[PDB]
Image (tube, coloured by chain):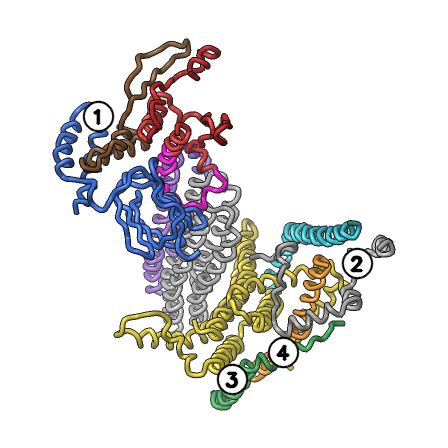
Chain colours: A green, B blue, C red, F purple, G orange, H yellow, I brown, J cyan
Amino acid sequence: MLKRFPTPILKVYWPFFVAGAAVYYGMSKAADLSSNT
Amino acid sequence: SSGLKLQFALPHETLYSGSEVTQVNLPAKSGRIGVLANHVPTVEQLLPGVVEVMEGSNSKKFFISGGFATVQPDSQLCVTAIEAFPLESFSQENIKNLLAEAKKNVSSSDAREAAEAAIQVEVLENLQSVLK
Amino acid sequence: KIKMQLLRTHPNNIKLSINGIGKDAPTFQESALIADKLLSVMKAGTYPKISIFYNDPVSSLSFEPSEKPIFNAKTIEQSPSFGKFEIDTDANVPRDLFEYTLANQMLTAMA
Amino acid sequence: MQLVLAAKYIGAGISTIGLLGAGIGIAIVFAALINGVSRNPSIKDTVFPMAILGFALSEATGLFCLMVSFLLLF
Amino acid sequence: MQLVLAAKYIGAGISTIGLLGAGIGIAIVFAALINGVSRNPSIKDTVFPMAILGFALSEATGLFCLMVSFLLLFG
Amino acid sequence: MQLVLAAKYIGAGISTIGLLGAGIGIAIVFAALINGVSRNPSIKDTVFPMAILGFALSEATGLFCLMVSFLLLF
Amino acid sequence: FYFMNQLTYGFLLMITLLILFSQFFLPMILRLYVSRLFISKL
Amino acid sequence: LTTFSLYTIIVLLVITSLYTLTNNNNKIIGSRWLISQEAIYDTIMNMTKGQIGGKNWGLYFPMIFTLFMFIFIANLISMIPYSFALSAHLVFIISLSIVIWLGNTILGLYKHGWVFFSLFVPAGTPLPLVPLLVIIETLSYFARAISLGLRLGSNILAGHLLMVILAGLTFNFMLINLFTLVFGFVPLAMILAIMMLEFAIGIIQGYVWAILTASYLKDAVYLH
Amino acid sequence: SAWRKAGISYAAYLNVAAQAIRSSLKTELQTASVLNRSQTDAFYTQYKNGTAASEPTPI
Amino acid sequence: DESILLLTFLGFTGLVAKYLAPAYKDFADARMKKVSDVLNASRNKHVEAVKD
Amino acid sequence: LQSTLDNIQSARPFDELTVDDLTKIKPEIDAKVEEMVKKGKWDVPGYKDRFGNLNVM
């Protein structure tokens, strides 16, 4: 099919996944605070 | 490269030939232009004025009787003109004014003489800036 | 001497003859004055193609007749490499650079 | 109450002419693009996206203003 | 409801001069066009399609103006 | 309903001054036209048709603007 | 209402596309580059 | 179930449909369906090489690809009329931009620590305006964040809604008296030109996204 | 001022500039070389198509 | 209502099949022939380098 | 070398060779590709001269 190469995605691209988790938790606060509209 | 290759040329003796240089200052039709290390390729006709050449050393000041400044695209500036000039020795007001009034008198003659007379009037009044 | 050559074989072609040259190494005043006389009475600006024939000393015991073309000012805007150089439209720089090219090329031809 | 929808409609009216900055702006870029290629024909690929890139910078800013009309329209 | 369509009509009135950048815009593109063929004679076949590129999606912005002035007039 | 025709009339008033830009634009066109033909006498009536072309469908915007003013009278 | 829905499925597709393109779809073309250059250089 | 999540499924299926069925059995010659992604690879390669200019520049070359292609594909799907808005949810796109900006900040602060705030003094100034250039850089520091998403989807919220309402205009053009059938072609060509511009507001807006975040990655990884 | 229109060509313009700088020379250092630069003795005779002649004029 | 937009899309795809697809055909064909030409020429060249 | 010439004449499928066969004939291919991704030098040097960049810009 397609030859899998172990390309560095965790030891390179951690902080954008970290920011995605942080925006998910801030969105949890937002959609628990601003869904009573 | 850093710096600039200067090639100053006169019909009797070329003064600079491939010298490395920092700044030149020279009078063009669009005004007084200074050229530094890299530059836009540009052909500037040279009205008779003053050219100042600054290097790692100081800046030598020349009066110049006009010509062409030409920036070869590898940032090599050539100046192709006629007359050199010392610090201040080659010009004296006794030869300037006493001939200059006669030249203004020739400026009222017939057309071919009067045009060259007016040109020399303009050149002597440019030399007034060298009188400074 | 080249006048007495070419007048013997083509007296119809010759229209101007400069005399009184070879007494010294020529300076810019003589060549520039002839450059003015070419564009005051001969009207070389209308001419598309101009060539200068000079004598080229390759070494001391060798020589060469040589052609050296003079590009007119109309050609310079038609140059494929022309627009690289920033030139003005408001300063007539080809219309003066052509005359300066004629001046120094005839000076190199004479000297 | 009979005025607030009419006021939102005149608010859509006043919020319209901000695409004027679009109407000038992209103009000079193409103007510069013609002066980009007039004095140097063999560099045009160098500027053929790089002009139009700025196009999408200016156009979208013009396309800011009228959608602020549209959510003021609704 | 006696006032809303009147205010829509004046809103279409003030949404009309946003095509001001139409009347300048495309025009000054042609300005450089007349420049570009002047100082470069053999570039016309080059420039005018790209220039008409810089015509079309430069004037359609102005079209946006009057379609606002067409809709707030009607819809 | 006695108000709405007056609002149509003042709307036709404010929907009129868009010819500002067309009058500036065709003037800039003729400005570059004279400035391009003075630096090029040899090529005059090759460009002048394209000049009057850009003139015509640049002034078509102001034509649209005042006919919008006419229908906003209506 | 559906900020969680769009956001969560979008982020899942973001992680999918990052790891997916990186492990598969870029170096499958880089192999074409290196193969063409290794034939041409020999 | 969500039709937007189904749209993400369509995105991943077309992404499978750009390389896998494209590749005629792993051939050197690089067939016509492969020249597409070849040219896309090179126009992102020659972009971000000269953009960030790092000695280690290709390390962030993957993400700039996958931040491009998602925006490049999701603005070629809703172009089909009978669809729903993909990229016009400003909440999702601006959320993505906030994730990108915060990841940039975390990356630069882990690389530089305290001196990452050396970006706020870009060039030499006299004394009495040294902090002012700081302030409206800090005021521009999150304006860097917010606008980038708030551009593109608001383009798309201005995009397809445009092709909504003018369609209704041509729906309110052709139900009055039969004389609306004569010379009623120029609104159709006008909406045709709207779709012509809509391909631009897809493609070139995606490339705008890519080039601005390329500059943002260069500023975040290297201090000036 | 309109020497390009009324008077000399541009090479001749700078030549008149050269004679002006050489005329406003310092009389101490106005050497024989510079006076050699201003020694115009060339003569020109505009021949015609029938190999006719004018008188030799000192340019 | 929305069938007008799909009608514009049908006219656009008619213009695409008229105009763009032969140009992209010529573009892909030129790139294909160029790649095949250089790729075959390098092989024939080092064939002659063996023959040297 | 005569055998190499004879093998060269009948075994050039130059418009239809699979890159998997090139990986099979050279593990240097996959070695350089994998090291190139691990270092991250996505630029292929010496490529643009004989093979065009072919992009829009």
| Residue bearing the label numbered 3 | A23
| Residue bearing the label numbered 1 | B113
Q: Is residue C60 visible?
A: yes
Label pair 1/2, CB-CB below 8 angstroms? no
> Chain under label 2?
K
> Chain under label 3?
A
Where does the image place residue B48, in percent across and percent down from the top left?
A: 27, 40
What residue sits 37% from the left and 71% below the top?
Answer: H122
**Nearer to me, H209 or A16:** A16
| Real-space CA distance between mark 3 and mark 2, rounded to the nearest whole angstrom | 49 Å
| Real-space CA distance between mark 4 and mark 1, rounded to the nearest whole angstrom | 84 Å
| Label 4 residue SS | loop
| Label 2 residue SS | loop
Asked if both marks, 1 and 3, belong to the same chain, the answer given is no
Magenta span main SS:
loop
Q: Is residue F29 visible?
A: no
Q: Amino acid at mark 3?
A: Val
| Real-space CA distance between mark 1 and mark 3, rounded to the nearest whole angstrom | 86 Å
Asked if both marks, 4 and 1, belong to the same chain, the answer given is no
Asked if both marks, 3 and 2, belong to the same chain, the answer given is no
Query: Which image quadrant: the N terminus of chain H?
Result: bottom right
Where does the image place residue F22, in percent across and percent down from the top left?
A: 37, 49
